[PDB]
Length: 117
Length: 117
Image 1 (cartoon, rainbow over the protein chains, first blue to last red):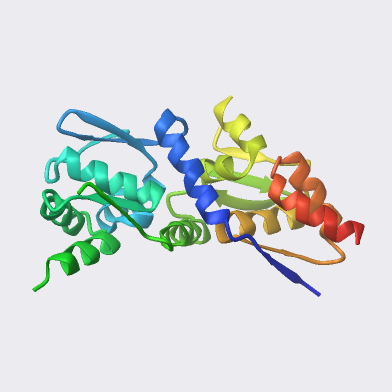
Image 2 (cartoon, rainbow over the protein chains, first blue to last red):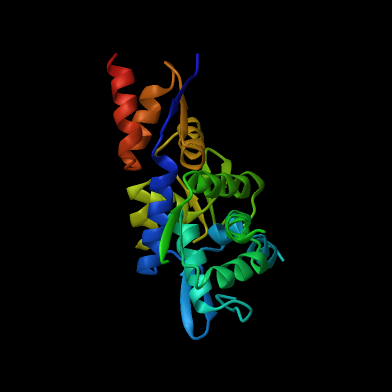
């Protein structure tokens, strides 16, 4: 009969490979531009993470985003590609604003819970 | 801050979204053709998963892959996008030869051991 063989580290290894690709600018199909900083990424990974980008890409190589800061987009990209959110009580309000406009629920829920109320 | 908050299930969330994309033919940038069967996929994900595909995509939009069976490619694509490989007594040597040619070392190790037993 069929045997299922699970691979515990597989999804981490796939994400690590996609992160290596943006870091080298290899096989990226899109560039986001925010405050003069370029972010080579994958439209597929952005859409799996952000309902804003999913909507944008399912209806250019370059997309200029004006409604978030470069600092916040950097935190949010690093999270999408590495699974770790780097944040301070100085920039958490900025990260939360951006996560709410880009519609990234994991981030927007954790940031708002830190600040609730 | 700065403080690195880990999200332990994020990598599986990303892969789940990539798998939904593939299952529907959405945001897929390449088609693999094997025995008249069409598999819409992402070259970034295949390269992250297979050293053969990494070299191929970093060296068209449709590729006919004649050196693996449709049965073996189906199993290996499901693996790439889900983290579980499903095999049987009857198809294990076939998945083992495809994993060696596609340079997917994690799969060939498990399959070799299954076959030798």
